[PDB]
Image (tube, rainbow, N blue to C red):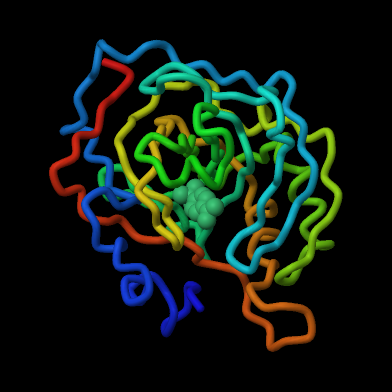
Length: 257
Ligand SMILES: NS(=O)(=O)c1ccc(B(O)O)cc1
Ligand SMILES: [Zn+2]
């Protein structure tokens, strides 16, 4: 099946997932000189005060930190969004080197990694229903650059040794996602898709302008993960990012003038 190698990577996906060539695919390059300030954007509200993480899982493409989404405990509201979106998981995309790894790019600049906080619209009852709708998902994207260490990431970093290979999971309770946010919540927003198969066009993308800084040692531990399962030839989990897709007729709006 699909992956990120030379023979199953992003350029192959359209053979099994024809929507890969659709009209609102993600990620995209963010042209900062063409994104327009939108005064019609309400303030963005990240309410992670009562977030309840459960588990961390290596799914052979990335690792997911999974949250209890049975109640409105961690929710995203406001900005371009109508209603309440519940946090279900977060994960990262990263590169083999610090000059690549992010999915979105900013004036063609690639960051070392990108964090995706994935939320689903409560009006559709559950995640599986939401991804079938144009406004089903909201994904908050946060760029990572290599610099000083991110203390709020270290709990994630420390547990990766226990989920090295595909299918491994570990208990991951009392993790506070607020420690992964930058100082400012200025953002760009546009309508797009999941960036991995099934590539469904169901995402309101909210991409923060300000990156967070992580240490070289921290990203180094990301790169020690494996795509493969236990007891198999080792493939380091690196470069698990999809490149920028054509913007087509979409407009990127900026929350900041
Ligand atoms: N990388 S992303 O946030 O756009 C994403 C999130 C979820 C799924 B999925 O549930 O298959 C795929 C891609
Ligand atoms: Zn992602």
